[PDB]
């Protein structure tokens, strides 16, 4: 029988965003670019801040929302880490890239996050899946 | 304590692939394209076959392997579904796109899969994370 | 005043494709996946064939078609080259990746192609722009 | 019988005078150097559309082989208020460009492939772009 993967808490993120800029609107769908302006990252094995990035989203009247984002985390001790997100909002899949010797274990991680309280859409908790 | 998401079995995939074509070999890294030639998909709420697609991979001597693939599933009842995979191999994150009325719930799904036995790398089991 | 780049003929492609599989049709757009099953490449630097690849296309309600493809050329001498196409159909922009010593000048090339006859769309001529 | 390949036409489309954040290198290894860089603003000019760049991000990889590949997205807001997504892909210093807008005035750009490069390579933030068709 299929055995599920384990889940281990990885980090929380409290992000700030500029207003979306809609560039392609039809009556049932809007596509936008949104600047990721900052935020704090906090987990057991790393922490830091978001220096910047961009999200591209497509939001349907049917309730679907697809988003793709790249942003960079700089850790407390100075490592730079690219975060690549792809999301069926509010569920977010995450990959990471860094050459930092202390953080390059993230290169092999698939993570997943969602806001624990949808009232507060920009506070997310993420989990390592494996 | 953060609450983890739930995991629900979504589908298995037994995929066939052509040999990789390595186009860029550099210090301790190879980048390749691989054709996805076919495969069977079996889950509680959908099933079908893989019509085709492509995987792009970057494999490092350091053990990291990043891959990104697109392939199309045609269900038994005739729906066409795009699968978008992104992976820190052997861990695979998945998104779906279809306008089929019976299967468009998948548009809101983030799934995750891995081979249950790495002996048989092309048989994977995937889970809906939410 | 602005001075334009120069154009030199790079190669032609006579491509074969599988069926177009439409996976997402709605009022805003029609989205399909299509396999590249083969093809003949001919140019001053090399002849070769298309090993395989995949194209994703979106036809908007507005009429415009945007396509994004990846495919692999293998030259007659066995070198592999990744071709990354992005198109405002029928105008195709092209980027390349190969570590082959004979052909690695392609890494630095931006190319552009289009079918000389729009009722014979699988034959295209491509130009190096710089 | 065979016809000789004939080239497309080039028409000047726009210039961009861009401002950028710091280049944040996240992955340095023997094979390549990978960075993320914010686009903080910029002036868009030319005969077809003018405006400013609202924001965007560029990802670049410099390989050991000497190639520099970059991929960027940024948003132009024109002087009259239309939003246009610009998708760039580059074998630096040569830049290919695609556009997305639903603006009625500017949606001709949806059918455009453009190409640009800095006319002065020691001023990398000023580029001139051409419509190819």
Image (spheres, coloured by chain):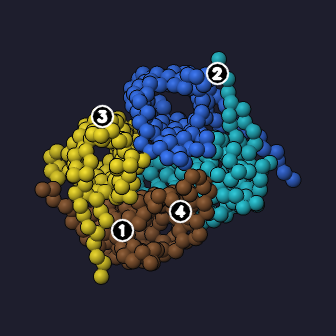
Chain colours: A yellow, B brown, C cyan, D blue
Where is residue D111, by image quadrant?
Answer: top right
Q: Secondary structure at mark 3?
A: strand
Q: Position of residue A24 (x, y in %)?
A: 40, 40
Q: Looking at this rendering, what residue extends furthest in the front direction? A: A101
Q: Looking at this rendering, what residue extends furthest in the bottom direction? A: A1
Question: Which residue position is annotated with label 4?
Answer: B54
**Viewer-nearest residue: D53 or C16:** D53
Q: Secondary structure at mark 1?
A: strand
Label 4: chain letter: B
Question: Which residue position is annotated with label 2?
Answer: C2
Q: CA distance from mark 3 to mark 1?
A: 32 Å
Q: How would you rate the neighbour count of disc 1 (Cα within 10 Å): few for under 14, some for 14-19, many for 20 or more?
A: many
The verdict on a common chain for dots 1 and 4 is yes
Where is residue A39, by image quadrant?
Answer: top left
Q: Is residue B127 visible?
A: yes
Q: Looking at this rendering, what residue extends furthest in the left direction? A: B1
Q: Are marks 1 and 2 in contact (CB under 8 Å)?
A: no
Q: Quadrant of the N terminus of chain B?
A: bottom left
Q: Quadrant of the C terminus of chain B?
A: bottom left
In this rendering, would A130 be left or right of B38? left
Q: How would you rate the neighbour count of disc 2 (Cα within 10 Å): few for under 14, some for 14-19, many for 20 or more?
A: few
Residue shown at 46% from the left, 74% from the top = B122
Q: Position of residue A121 (x, y in %)?
A: 20, 45
Q: How would you rate the neighbour count of disc 3 (Cα within 10 Å): few for under 14, some for 14-19, many for 20 or more?
A: some
Question: Which residue position is annotated with label 3?
Answer: A37
Q: Is residue D75 visible?
A: no
In this rendering, would C63 be left or right of B4? right
Q: CA distance from mark 4 to mark 2?
A: 40 Å
Q: Are marks 4 and 3 in contact (CB under 8 Å)?
A: no
Label 3: chain letter: A
Q: CA distance from mark 3 to mark 2?
A: 35 Å
In the picture, the disc for residue B113 is 1
């Amino acid at each position: 029988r299929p055995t599920p993967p384990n889940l281990e808490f990885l980090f929380s993120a409290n992000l700030t965003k500029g207003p979306a800029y809609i560039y392609d609107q039809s009556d049932a769908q809007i596509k936008a670019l949104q600047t990721l302006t900052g935020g704090i990252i906090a987990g057991p094995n790393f922490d830091g801040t978001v220096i910047g990035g961009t999200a591209l989203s497509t939001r349907g009247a049917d309730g679907t929302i697809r988003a793709d984002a790249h942003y960079l985390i700089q850790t407390s001790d100075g490592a730079n880490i690219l975060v690549t997100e792809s999301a069926a909002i509010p569920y977010v899949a995450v990959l990471f890239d860094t050459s930092s010797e202390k953080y390059n274990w993230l290169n092999n991680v698939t993570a997943w996050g969602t806001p624990p309280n949808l009232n507060e859409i920009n506070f997310l908790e993420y989990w390592q899946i494996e």
